[PDB]
Amino acid sequence: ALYEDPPDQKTSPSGKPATLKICSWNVDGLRAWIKKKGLDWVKEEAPDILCLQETKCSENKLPAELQELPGLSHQYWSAPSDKEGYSGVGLLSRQAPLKVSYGIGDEEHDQEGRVIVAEFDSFVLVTAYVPNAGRGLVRLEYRQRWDEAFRKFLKGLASRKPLVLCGDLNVAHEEIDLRNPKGNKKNAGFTPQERQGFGELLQAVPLADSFRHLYPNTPYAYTFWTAMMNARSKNVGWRLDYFLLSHSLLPALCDSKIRSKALGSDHCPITLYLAL
DNA sequence: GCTGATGCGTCGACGGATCC
DNA sequence: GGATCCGTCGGACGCATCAGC
């Protein structure tokens, strides 16, 4: 029922040590999260790259603390065009990315502030906040439109350069990736359609599920728990937040964590260790 | 202009039907 | 009544907007 994450494995299968520490994290409000001491946690995790989801902040109103980070000088933000207070991703890197695109190059799917590409010397990092399917599955057909457009996008981008996809992808792939699989076959985030899109993306590109690639049988491994019904303490959660790697990066994979003791948000941080 | 009130977006506990 | 399968619904958040001062 409860979960304890394994010790950090900082050496690749080949014995090579880790060189990249990417940490992604849905903050459920960037200003509330900072008020909840989120960055004191981040400073201790000391990532090379910090990716953020559901910032719900405009580049104007960013808190000041976001400056007091001397290890992640290069910070790239992203918000919905229409209206304040929704969605919105961030990406903070220690070193300057060669390039920084935004969105998946598709007018329909870029208005909401969900995707940030970031090209590096040996790979490209995409951090995402995939559109939720919504209560009542009222936004479910949008999400399918998006799934295929995002699959097609990333497939292309992994042609050109090894791909690291991370962030809240808002589906739980298998029954194992959530606490209550049956009572949610029709909930946003575990529909047949959401689950098959992900499965399709996993192999069409192709991408590997960093965590389940090293811990393919370990359940109760959760990145999100709801805040209505005591779920986090009881460990009733979903695995909504991923690291998907091109198979080329698989020999470089040291470990993939789920830092479940870190509060600040209804999600918890997930860290990737890649030896590049 | 300030301040709370109400809203929008983001599911597991409970109870009722059913076959045994 | 007890096991399973399914349907509804109160309820927590962080944000914005808006009515009432």
Image: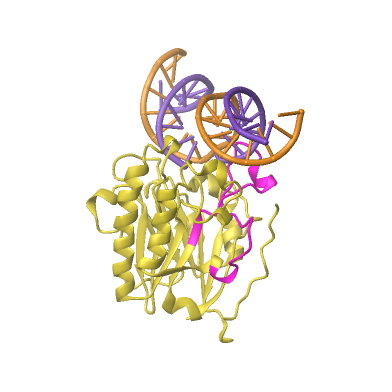
Chain colours: A yellow, B purple, C orange
**Residue A33 in view, yes or no:** yes
Residue A95 or residue A229, whichever sits in front:
A229
Numbered disc total? 0
Picture quadrant of residue A122: bottom left
A110 sits left or right of A256 in the view? left
Q: Position of residue A89 (x, y in %)?
A: 41, 53
Residue B9 or residue A181, whichever sits in front:
A181
Above or below, comparing residue A248 to residue A5 in the picture? below
Q: Position of residue A272 (x, y in %)?
A: 53, 69
Question: At 70% from the left edge and 53% from the top edge, which residue is drawn?
Answer: A2
Q: Position of residue A151 (x, y in %)?
A: 33, 61
Question: At 40% from the left edge and 40% from the top edge, which residue is drawn?
Answer: A85
Question: At 43% from the left edge and 60% from the top edge, which residue is drawn?
Answer: A199
Give yes or no for residue A215 being in the magenta stretch: yes
Question: At 29% from the left edge and 50% from the top edge, which residue is drawn?
Answer: A109
**Residue A101 in view, yes or no:** no
Give yes or no for residue A139 being in the magenta stretch: no
Q: Position of residue C13 (x, y in %)?
A: 55, 37
Main SS of residues in magenta = loop
For the record, the magenta segment spans A213-242
Picture quadrant of residue A83: top left
A144 sits left or right of A28 in the view? left
